[PDB]
Image: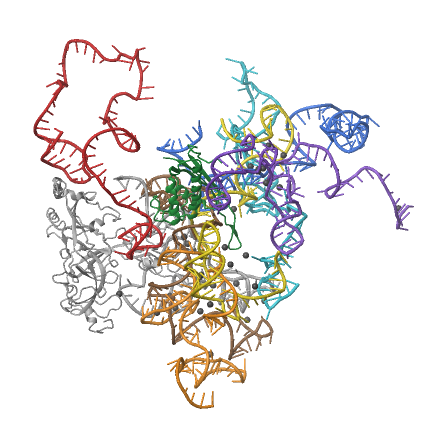
Chain colours: B green, C red, E brown, F orange, G yellow, H cyan, I blue, J purple
Amino acid sequence: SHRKFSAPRHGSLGFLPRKRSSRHRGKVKSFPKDDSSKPVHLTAFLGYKAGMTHIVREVDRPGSKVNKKEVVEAVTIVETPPMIVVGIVGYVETPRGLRTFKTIFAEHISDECKRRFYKNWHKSKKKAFTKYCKKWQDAAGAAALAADFSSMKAYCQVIRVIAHTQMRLLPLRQKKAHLMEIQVNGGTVAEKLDWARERLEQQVPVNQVFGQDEMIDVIGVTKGKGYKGVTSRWHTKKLPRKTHRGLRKVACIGAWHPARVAFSVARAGQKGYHHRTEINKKIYKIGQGYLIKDGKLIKNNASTDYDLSDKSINPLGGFVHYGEVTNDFVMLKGCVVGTKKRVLTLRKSLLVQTKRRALEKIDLKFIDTTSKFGHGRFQTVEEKKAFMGPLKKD
Amino acid sequence: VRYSLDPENPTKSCKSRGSNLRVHFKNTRETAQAIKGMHIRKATKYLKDVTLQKQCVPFRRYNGGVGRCAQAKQWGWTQGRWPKKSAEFLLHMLKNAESNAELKGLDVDSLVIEHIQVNKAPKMRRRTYRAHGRINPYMSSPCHIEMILTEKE
RNA sequence: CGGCCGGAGAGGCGGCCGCCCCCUCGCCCGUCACGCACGCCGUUCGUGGGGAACCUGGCGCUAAACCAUUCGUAGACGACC
RNA sequence: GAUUGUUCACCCACUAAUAGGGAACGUGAGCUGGGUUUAGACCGUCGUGAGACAGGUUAGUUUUACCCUACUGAUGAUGUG
RNA sequence: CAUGAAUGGAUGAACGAGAUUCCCACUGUCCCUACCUACUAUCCAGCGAAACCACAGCCAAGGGAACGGGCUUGGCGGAAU
RNA sequence: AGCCUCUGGCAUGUUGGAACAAUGUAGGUAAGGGAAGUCGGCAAGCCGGAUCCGUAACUUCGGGAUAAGGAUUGGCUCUAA
RNA sequence: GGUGGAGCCGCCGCAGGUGCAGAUCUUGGUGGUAGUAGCAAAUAUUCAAACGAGAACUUUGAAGGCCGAAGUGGAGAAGGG
RNA sequence: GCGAAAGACUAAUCGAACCAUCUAGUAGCUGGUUCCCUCCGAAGUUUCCCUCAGGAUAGCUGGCGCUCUCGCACACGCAGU
RNA sequence: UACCCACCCGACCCGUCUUGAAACACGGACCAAGGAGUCUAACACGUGCGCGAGUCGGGGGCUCGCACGAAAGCCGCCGUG
RNA sequence: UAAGGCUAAAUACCGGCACGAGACCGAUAGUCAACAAGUACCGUAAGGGAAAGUUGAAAAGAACUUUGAAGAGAGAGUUCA
Ligand SMILES: [Mg+2]
Ligand SMILES: [Mg+2]
Ligand SMILES: [Mg+2]
Ligand SMILES: [Mg+2]
Ligand SMILES: [Mg+2]
Ligand SMILES: [Mg+2]
Ligand SMILES: [Mg+2]
Ligand SMILES: [Mg+2]
Ligand SMILES: [Mg+2]
Ligand SMILES: [Mg+2]
Ligand SMILES: [Mg+2]
Ligand SMILES: [Mg+2]
Ligand SMILES: [Mg+2]
Ligand SMILES: [Mg+2]
Ligand SMILES: [Mg+2]
Ligand SMILES: [Mg+2]
Ligand SMILES: [Mg+2]
Ligand SMILES: [Mg+2]
Ligand SMILES: [Mg+2]
Ligand SMILES: [Mg+2]
Ligand SMILES: [Mg+2]
Ligand SMILES: [Mg+2]
Ligand SMILES: [Mg+2]
Ligand SMILES: [Mg+2]
Ligand SMILES: [Mg+2]
Ligand SMILES: [Mg+2]
Ligand SMILES: [Mg+2]
Ligand SMILES: [Mg+2]
Ligand SMILES: [Mg+2]
Ligand SMILES: [Mg+2]
Ligand SMILES: [Mg+2]
Ligand SMILES: [Mg+2]
Ligand SMILES: [Mg+2]
Ligand SMILES: [Mg+2]
Ligand SMILES: [Mg+2]
Ligand SMILES: [Mg+2]
């Protein structure tokens, strides 16, 4: 017979080889279509989720109840030190797919970049890229990497740039840099290419990839939660109190005549640590790490013009569970996938964004920096000694 | 008595057997084939780490329900355990044979465990008591272990 | 034997130039010869085949992986960072 | 949602709409056990009687998965020196 | 249909682990689930059963003892767990 | 009564070690709503001791009755009896 | 051919308790399941020493604990021997 | 027997104990029924039966024969025509 | 021919009751040993043999302690029947 | 010739004592019992009631050396084995 009272299904099938993700750094599965008229730029970046906080801003969407009112928005902060370019890679279009031509790494490489090459490091001799680097000064310093750029100029169509993070500038215990191919959505290969030939061994800060109030996509790995019941995983109903054998299950799996349990029935399994691609997140502010000209420009982190304190986005006691953010960052509206410290990939929008809620230029009026290690009550440490004042420990 | 697979050179080969020992034949067979073909001193160490849980014994034939482990990767398996009694019992027998080769006049440090074999033994009887007054047989499974070390170097 | 090309769709191939030494070979004719094995079968080649083990010379080489340990961003164990 | 063991029914209320059905009249080693449908009892009718009654009524044990498969997750696997 | 007088009729204080209905109080019964604890399960050393078993174990449709795992035709199939 | 302790008696009731997954079995707690839950308020929680007050219908005049409904309650220093 | 260590068969006649796959057959034996289910009711153990081939489990000391006098304490009946 | 009555209880047994025997009780009803080869080869219909899951009798079957015929230049007989 | 392997074609698991079984009908994990138309009496027909209007056979008797014998042989008994 | 009485022989013997034999069974057979069998064991009791034969010819039943806490081994020896 049929279902008495119809109801939607629990949880989308559009996600459902719901397994522990096979990668860790968020892999970009599609880069934006390269319009070959606009100048050359990078399409992706690589940041680290740090924490969250309150924002205060004025709204401009006329006709709404909250036009010219102040709202609070929760924002993540993605600590994003400048990435380093090490190599370029060519791709050529085939019927069978999109094959890779020619990877050409620079003369130097790094130290952090070597880490990403061997599982155990301190046991090894650190020999990676020790004879490829030899090519970059001799007669063959023209054969294998000057006829190659001419080859990648003749037959290549799409050119990405292999670029690794700097793991030494972060508070993290990791030192294995994160490499990633970041496609160059410029125009005219050989201009797409005689730009990355230049930026070999070079820094790339976040203000080159991304601009303020730009719709990007965040590509990371869900927070992990282990084996979970059908009730947590697929968010089913709980059976009534009286059920003899468990009440956190699905009473009926399937019907008798399809003698297999179906692909789409809810089951217990791993939950969390899936790969997800969040789209259409907005940037509220591109940051700038506390650099030195005389000393410690911590001011230029959370000092919006409307309050002009000298806060760093670091709250009191740093961002709980992760540390203090000390270089550039991007402030994102709402929540991003992943836990603290997770490697986050930041892609530019594949959509032509022309809505009213987007394109909305943003003015920060106050950035909350009170401690997240409990119920913080007051923002900066000097303000603490404006209240209570002289403590006993003096 | 005779063994199966009597040795190539009866001159440079010592033997040792045990009959009716209280180990579990499905474990002592797994730990007997893992040590098979090794060189004596390499195996004495291996059988001590089986006790200290530093190297496993990969469970190939009798693997039902046996859990995965990390040290199983060396043998190219997934399942492996640390059968401690099984290690201790073919450790005496690996130590008895090391003396039979001493008395025969051989080179102790060039002996390679070439043949080794574990057979089921006449089972023991106990009884467990089960619901509704049933009485099941709660039996043991002993074994006859026997091994032949050769001089191969 | 050296150099310059051309070819990328999974290229795997050619092409085009210098120099050394050597040979004179497709077609008609003469001229003889070549175990003529005594009527008999798997003949004739792509074959320096493909793969697996071992005896000469020249140039180069100089590891990582897994365990043990540690970490949790991960966990039923495995696995993973 | 109210009533009902109910399927079915009827109403209240909301809504964009409160369409109709199949999957062993989907689905008890998934549940519940209200209804049927044991043994206890109670009435009415019938039967001389034991008893009968799709006539009511109240009380009445709901087992076993470790096997193969499917499915969900989890290690791996031959190849690629 | 088919009540009714010791096959007892009508009442009824107290009493009832007797059967219903309603209201107040209360509440994770529910909207809608969440987390915390103990013992498990989980992995390990030790010790070790049983029911069950033709052969066995991926599907669609067809026919067929009129609902196949095996047969026909398709779909497909990768060790050990 | 329960709860803690002397006298006396044991060594966690046929094992240990490592972890804190899902389901469980026992215990707990939940914002707002409060029986909309279900066949039914199933289970659970509300009440709870004492002192002071206060007490209905009904009645076989014994009861109902701890009806219902309210208040008070520690420590200390006194006083009175 | 082998192992085995004391008896055995061919033909003509006679006599049978005379030929097994099966009977939820009888008795005995052995697998797959499986090194799996399991060794989870009453809060609890730890340190040092002794003994010893060998100690989480014995013994002594120390510490923490429970039974809490309607006992896990001290004595008897029936029963046991 | 015993029952403040449920057919309750009477040594894990009760709408009628346990033990041995009569006993290999009876079964128109299930289950099984042991070597080869060769030749022949059915029935599910008739009448009667407390007959309708069985028998009795008819048929259909086989075995055993016998009486003759004459392919022994020299045949009457029969027939799903 | 029989051991292993390869291939092309064929090929559903046996026993059973059944109009119909590979059956989503039942018995069957596996292997050993055991295991089911017997004897007696009474008829009936067929067949072999002795004698033949007769022919026995029993019970008795006469001959052994048996070795073979509790046999064989013999008896107006032989016809009482 | 009743109402009173005695009696050897041929006749019967799955108990008992003592024997003899067999076209019998041969250790799941033959008695339940080839053995410490009506024993072990079950049941309150009446009763029920098993399994279990074979070293060699002679114990000549493995001294001694060695490894091990020991069980077990390695050599040696006994033997026709
Ligand atoms: Mg519908
Ligand atoms: Mg229940
Ligand atoms: Mg916080
Ligand atoms: Mg038990
Ligand atoms: Mg009992
Ligand atoms: Mg149904
Ligand atoms: Mg079901
Ligand atoms: Mg059920
Ligand atoms: Mg009911
Ligand atoms: Mg009833
Ligand atoms: Mg009446
Ligand atoms: Mg009447
Ligand atoms: Mg398990
Ligand atoms: Mg405990
Ligand atoms: Mg005890
Ligand atoms: Mg609440
Ligand atoms: Mg309700
Ligand atoms: Mg409802
Ligand atoms: Mg209750
Ligand atoms: Mg009242
Ligand atoms: Mg003999
Ligand atoms: Mg016989
Ligand atoms: Mg037989
Ligand atoms: Mg207590
Ligand atoms: Mg005492
Ligand atoms: Mg029948
Ligand atoms: Mg039928
Ligand atoms: Mg069928
Ligand atoms: Mg039947
Ligand atoms: Mg007289
Ligand atoms: Mg016997
Ligand atoms: Mg025998
Ligand atoms: Mg016997
Ligand atoms: Mg024997
Ligand atoms: Mg024997
Ligand atoms: Mg012999």
Q: Viewed as shown, does residue A318 lie left or right of J20?
A: left
Q: B2 or F24: which is nearer to us?
A: B2
Residue A249 appears in the figure: no
On the image, which quarter does residue A350 sit in?
Answer: bottom left
- The residue nearer to you, when weighing A307 against A384, is A384
Q: Is residue A46 above or below residue E54?
A: below
H10 or G39: nearer the eye? G39
The C terminus of chain A sits in image quarter: bottom left
The spot of residue A156 in percent (x, y) is 14, 44
Residue J29 position within the rendered picture, expressed as x and y whole percent measured from the top left: 62, 39
How many numbered marks does the figure carry?
Answer: 0
Q: Quadrant of residue G5?
A: top right
Q: Is F59 rendered above or below residue A211?
A: below
Q: Position of residue G60 (x, y in %)?
A: 48, 60
Q: Is residue F42 above or below residue A86?
A: below
- Residue A89 visible in rendering: yes
Question: Where H13 falls versus J5 (above or below)?
Answer: below
* G41 and E13: which is toward the camera: G41
* The quarter of the displayed image where residue C56 is located: top left
Percent from the top left, x then y, of residue J1? 91, 46
The quadrant of the rendered image in which ligand 25 is seen is bottom right
In the rendered view of the protein, which quadrant contains the N terminus of chain A? bottom left
- In this rendering, position of residue A207 left or right of residue F7: left
